[PDB]
Length: 292
Length: 290
Ligand SMILES: NC(=O)c1ccc[n+]([C@@H]2O[C@H](COP(=O)([O-])OP(=O)(O)OC[C@H]3O[C@@H](n4cnc5c(N)ncnc54)[C@H](O)[C@@H]3O)[C@@H](O)[C@H]2O)c1
Ligand SMILES: NC(=O)c1ccc[n+]([C@@H]2O[C@H](COP(=O)([O-])OP(=O)(O)OC[C@H]3O[C@@H](n4cnc5c(N)ncnc54)[C@H](O)[C@@H]3O)[C@@H](O)[C@H]2O)c1
Ligand SMILES: Nc1nc(N)c(NC(=O)Nc2ccc(C(=O)N[C@@H](CCc3nnn[nH]3)C(=O)O)cc2)c(=O)[nH]1
Ligand SMILES: Nc1nc(N)c(NC(=O)Nc2ccc(C(=O)N[C@@H](CCc3nnn[nH]3)C(=O)O)cc2)c(=O)[nH]1
Image (tube, rainbow over all chains, first blue to last red; front, side, top):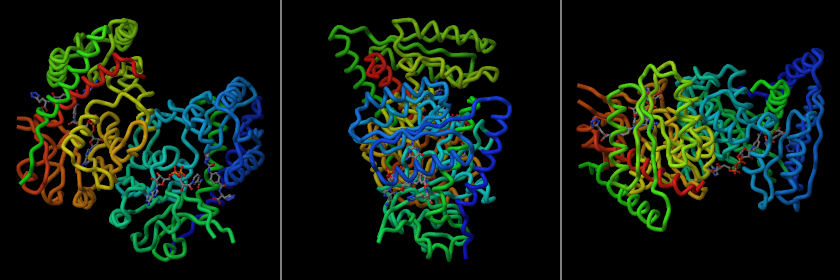
């Protein structure tokens, strides 16, 4: 039976490290770090996630505010707010929760965050630098997926990894970290990485996952991954968070079935989710210090 | 037996499209495109490739100058030259031929070229836009590999593709173009892409290539791809240019000629496509589409 990695427990520990680093940063006489999250509209999952981000900020001693705006806001109005916060010396970290309404262009919003306050890693310069293996602010969820693999001791070099999903904020950066060179400014995992997505036929996904030592599913599809596609002893990291039915929450992985064939497994909830919040706190203290 | 895709004949068409577009662009009153190439030192393959580049520019109506500097040049002096060209209103496309001598930070040189003149697609903003599937200058060898696949009509959507190599300038953008979404600003190939590299064991490479509808080799290793790794009928695209003793790619051409459906020769395969797509990017830059 597979070891269930608690993302809740790993995240909680990482927050402690961030907390220690913050009180030391403050005791050295620097300003306490402040994080500003802009929330647009009323997606319920967005409000949970932002709520968890602001709770972790309190836990790690970072000041925070959530600024909620209605979905009917215009792109100029959001840009004005972002520019205002870009210019508030008290604001070290600034993120806009995604997704945004169809009339707001995400990339223009993401690029409008001052790159030094870009705790999301979503600004195009930050994406370029990550894709060139330079020093960069890493996006939280992919960096959380990496920390689960690293802090658990699961090896990546020369190993087979399948990522199901290619979103620019989740699947693509995960795939970029795991396959890239360990020797570069920002090291990578030196793994052999298969990117699959909505046009991968389910029979072809199986033909690759069977080869895999790590399967990372970020597709948003319940039971996408099941025990017959999983090689024995392999690590399965479930990035999906899907609302199904009374209302429940699952990942992409058939947790119970894969449990019996994986060597490692991530639950949903309490897996990759809490790790995203933790790495965001790390990015905020990194941004407050002005290291990049 | 395996169709041998002619790199020279496809680039001929692409180049004719460009001469057409440049002539229309000039006739309607605009300035003729100008491409500046900076070349450092005396790598004989570099001078060959630059010469091929300016030869192709001349036949498609694009003016061009090669600027040669010695290997002993200093990074500060190259930065001067690049900044002067960024501000020369005649220069539409500017590119610095790689590799650069070991004492020069290639990344810092690439980011020095202004992105609107970055016909290589190597400035960090162009790398990021490409990785976001946005309108960008695509790098010439990656775009050439794509054009070979599209214009030969080899399907990619839903197909297994392996790329051997992860270099930021060739292997990585090939993998990016091929796995990405056909419906985005810059479309991709919607394939299932495996990225292999130097720490991939051969057994695991072969276990992934026997599944591959398209194998793309950009590793710079002679005889890497052999017929036992290739499934019957699959397309094999040889990006590597290896000076063995002669000039050959990564593939075992004669052997894989028997198992593959399609194959590309070295030379005369991807090589000419790189020169062809650089011509596309130069007319794109002159139009200031971005
Ligand atoms: N911290 C966390 O755990 C966290 C945070 C955010 C999102 N998520 C989840 O992780 C994923 C992130 O992706 P997103 O929501 O940004 O992307 P998205 O919703 O825009 O697209 C999802 C991706 O799934 C892929 N996909 C769809 N069907 C597939 C199939 N049959 N096989 C393989 N791939 C398939 C798509 O091609 C696409 O790349 C989603 O599943 C989301 O629920 C998790
Ligand atoms: N330099 C040029 O002008 C030019 C032009 C077109 C094509 N190419 C070819 O493309 C290659 C890549 O371009 P570059 O020079 O920027 O890259 P590079 O020389 O930095 O490295 C090439 C790649 O090969 C990979 N590799 C090494 N051993 C491997 C193995 N056993 N299996 C799979 N992959 C392996 C490496 O991990 C690396 O990513 C070149 O070596 C060259 O032959 C070069
Ligand atoms: N700008 C921007 N926009 C974005 N969208 C993201 N991504 C993001 O925020 N992801 C995210 C996902 C899950 C969770 C979390 O807290 N997970 C808990 C369950 C809690 C719960 N509450 N209700 N249901 N579940 C769990 O998985 O156990 C926190 C954050 C970003 O990073 N930056
Ligand atoms: N900034 C920058 N720097 C770079 N280094 C590159 N890469 C690059 O230019 N690659 C490249 C490789 C081959 C050829 C070519 O012409 N191949 C022919 C001739 C064979 C031959 N050789 N000698 N005799 N015959 C063939 O393969 O058929 C053209 C370009 C770049 O794109 N931008």
